[PDB]
Each structure stands twice: as structure tokens, then as C-alpha cells.
Amino acid sequence: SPWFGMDIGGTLVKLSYFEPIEQEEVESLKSIRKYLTSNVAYRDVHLELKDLTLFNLHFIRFPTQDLPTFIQMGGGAYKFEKLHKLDELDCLVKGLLYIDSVSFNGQAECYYFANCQKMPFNLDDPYPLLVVNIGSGVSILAVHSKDNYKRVTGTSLGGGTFLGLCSLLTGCESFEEALEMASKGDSTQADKLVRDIYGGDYERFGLPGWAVASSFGNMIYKEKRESVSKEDLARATLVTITNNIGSVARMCAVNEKINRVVFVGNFLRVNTLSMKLLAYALDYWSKGQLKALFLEHEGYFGAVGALLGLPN
Amino acid sequence: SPWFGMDIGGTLVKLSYFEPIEQEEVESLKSIRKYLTSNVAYRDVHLELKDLTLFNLHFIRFPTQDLPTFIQMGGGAYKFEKLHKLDELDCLVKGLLYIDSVSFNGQAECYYFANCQKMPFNLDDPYPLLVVNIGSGVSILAVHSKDNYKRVTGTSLGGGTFLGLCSLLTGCESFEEALEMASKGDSTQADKLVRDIYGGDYERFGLPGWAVASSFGNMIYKEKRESVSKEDLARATLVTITNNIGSVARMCAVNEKINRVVFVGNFLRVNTLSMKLLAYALDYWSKGQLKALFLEHEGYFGAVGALLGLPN
Image (cartoon, rainbow over all chains, first blue to last red; front, side):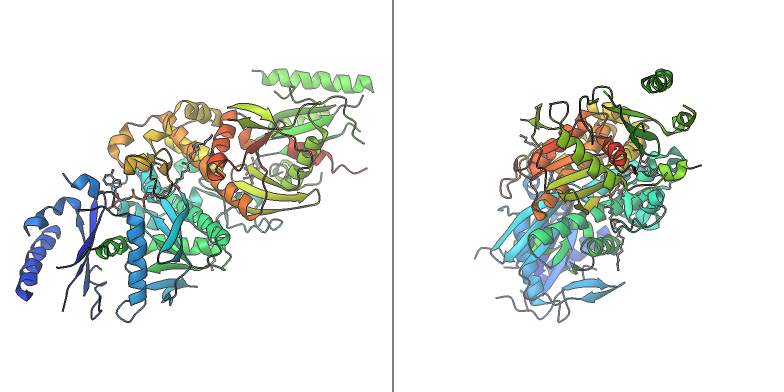
């Protein structure tokens, strides 16, 4: 009766719970969940939604290893049996539409960066819609209605491609390590810009000097290979990923004739930096004809999408 | 009067010469060019073209440093002044059309891989045409006629991106080192395949298990990080590049409604392996609706494109 749905990845579980407005039972349940969370201590409450009717919504994440403890209290779930599975993407969609239709407590679930500061975007009649899911790789979904959507393409250069490389480039233990490393790096030391070839704008084919002519182009020169810092390659690594994703997304929006491109995925959660670089990139490839949109509950959509398949 | 046009890059010069059918002067010129080439000794003659009227064509390459010696006998030319420049791409186009219109001594200048072995392709009415130029980066040209064409997009992941990385991944001194390294590597040790997530085909969104889910996806696991050989990453590096290029090219062919996609660039010269991986990739993204085409004089087109701007 306490309604909920879990997003089970290979390292983490994302979960949404509906707190109805018995009382003692939920409380004691809440008390020992407080135990475990304060164990972990050695923004999830920011995204709580109140006074919403559903025929509160709380949002939490915790290691998959912590999950079996709750019994006494996607890709990951098949190996945790050690329930009925549901397609992450189907749950991503159903979940996404719901929250965006219900708003964020009278504020907007969808937003973008104006240029840069963040600003909202009414997305209440969202069809059609281009959803770019960035996990280890990227899958692009063209959504036409609540009951129709399909994966029209993808790229193998996603999150697993960035951390995968930076770990090889930097010895970085974790993702946020690479992020904050990237956050301090400068890509131009690694990549070759347009002006690195022509001295300036390639005006003939409408190319500015500041565009990236070659990812890691300057790393063919041992001179500059010794001269590049860990953080730059961390930075250099992420730039390429984002720029390529923006390019594919833009080409997709053109072919599928969709003007709204929202980015999601477990990859977008820890830092807004990932988000901004996509925003700059989609801006460049669509030449401003496309804005990038993002969601505040990015990461729990699968979780809630699982919540609404509940059988009664 | 001995007509010729040079392609001057930052490391090499590509040059085409028209041997008309005086005789002593060309001979002695030829003799001391034989000197220098036999100095270097410490397929260019295969591409010679004979009995062609032009209102023989010989094809040669040599280090830019060797060039000034000939006086007594693109990007690179501006720094060699130490003539009138001409846009490499304009010369690429003019050069390409010419040779493909004139055939290859009664054999085909254009070919593709049948599936894999190589087989020819009549390309005598080539408009429209998608030319994918892979240098340090990739520029895609949509050609509509001999006098009309424009760069419709590009990607920053080209040759400079591959050697750039492998050098950082492998300590490889040169390109052919990385190539033959790649030639011995296996990418699956680095990248995460579809089946690495679902155990098999993702049949729901029509995804086979053997597709690459994440470039270097398996390199987030230190286990597999120690377990990957230099050659695989060399291999792993090239796969991603080719697959991304095929994807962009395919999306471009769709939007520009061109069915013929030919690949060129200094990057395609040393090995057919680069070529085959593009052929497999364009095959996958267009689902066989597109074949990849290649040229036998790939690399001298700029050179000859410069030959036909000669003023008289």
C-alpha cells in the first residue's frame, strides 16, 4: 500500500515513494530509514513534491548493496534477485511525462540556460519531444505521444566513454574526481582549434577560429603532450563527448522535425557543468535554433516510471 | 611548361606532374629526382596514368623539407614561403571530379568492398555526392555540380584525434605504429558491448548484442584496465572514430538526400584497414542502404586540383 518504484542500476538504486496524507507505521519505517541514511553520512529532499493528488513524492538514492536490508525494515535488478522487470526507457518516458505534467510544486520541472543563468520552460504540451539519455552510452528517443515513442539512434560516446578515458588518462578513482578535474582543466591545450591551422577564422566555409578542428589534435605533438595537465584532458575528454552528443542530437532534431531537445541520464546528476557544455554545444550545431532543456528530477524518472506500473 | 600542382601539408608534400608525349631536359630532371628518391630509400608509381589527353600523370610525395632543393633542380604552404595559395577543399573537389571522369587507365578510379573484397563502382555522373574528408578532423562536403558544393558539417574526431589518443594511450611514436598496433588489437576488451549489459540482443529497441554500447565502457573497471593491451586501445581508439564518422556521414546523407558517400583524406592512405572500418560502419548506420566508396588516387586529389588552376 505504500506505493513506490525502484530504479536499480549496477551501483545504485533510485527510488520514489508516495507519502499519503498507519501513521505510526509509516513513522517507524521512516525512523529506521533515518538510521541507515545517517549511517551513509560517514538535493534529494529538495525535490520533494507536496499537496499533489495521484488518482507527497519523496526521492532517494542508495547503494544497491543497502537494498536487501529494507525487506526486514533496470539493468541492476536482474542480478539482484540473488518482482517483475520493466524497460528502463519505458519507465523513463512514463515517469518523465508525469512529473512534467504535474509541475514542481507550482514551479517548473523543465528549464534551460539563458545567454548564463538558469530559467524555466513551460513544457506542458510536450509532444513531440527529443529525449537524449546519457548513461554509459546515449540513446535518443523521439517521443510523439504518451503511448508512442521509439529509439531513433544513439552514440557509443557517453558517460562510460568519458570516465573510461579519464581514468586511463588521469588515474582518477571516481567520476566526481574527473568532473572537478575537468572543472579545472582547459581543453585547448589538448585539442587543436581552427585557428591552430589557419591562424584565425576559416571564413570560406564559415568556420570560426575558436571551433575545435581536431579533438586532441595538439596531443600528437610530444611537446604539448608533456605540457598538458591531468585536468585539461579531463576537461578535454568531456568537451569532445558533449560536442559530439550535441551534434548527433541536432542532426536528429532536424531529421525527426522536433524542436525540443531535453537531456537526461544518470550522467547529468552530479554536476551542472555537464549540462552547460551540452547547452553550448546544441546552441552551436543548431546555431541557436535549438535550446537545451533539462529537468529538476533528472535521474528519478525511471524510478517513478516504475511506480506507475503498479498492479492493483 | 612542365605542368604540376603541389599539395603542401605540415609534414608532407603531395605532387602530380604531367609528362607530355626538351626530351633531354625532362630526362635529366628525372635523373636527379631519382637521386633524391633513392636518398629517401634509407604504390605511387602504381597510380601513374598514361595515354590521357589533357586539353602522363605521375604522382609523388616527399617531405616538405625536401622541397626547396627542387628549385635548383594547403596549410603547409603559407609557412614554407620562408606562388598563390588555393583552398585545399576547392582543389580536392576539382581534382577528384577530373580523375574520376578520366578513369584509371581504363580501370575504375572508384571502388567499394563487397560483402569482403574490393570491387569497382562506375562513378561517371557523380552528382550529387557526399565527400567525407578525414584529416586531423573531418569535413563533409555535399557536391551538387562541378561549380557548386559546400561544407554542410563536420566532426572534430578525425585522424588527429586517433593518433593523438593512441600516442597518449600507447606511447606510439608514429601513425603506422598505431595502425599496425590497432591491426593487432581487439576493441571489445576496452569497450562495453550491448550484450555486456543485457547479456544479449536488446531486441526491444532493435539492438543486437554485438553493437558497442559504450566506447571504452569496460575501461571504467580497473580489473579490465590492467587487462587491456596497447594494441586493443589502439584498436579500441580507431573503432570509435570510424563508427562515429559513419554515423555522422549517414545522418548527413539522409538530410542532404545524397546516396553516394565517398571517403577521402590524408588519413586513408597508409592502410586499407581504416577504409574497411568505415565500410562496416556506414553499412550499419544506413543498414546497408549506403555503400562506402573510395578512390585509388586518394591523397593526390588536392595535388592535381592545384594542377588545374594553372594560369596561361
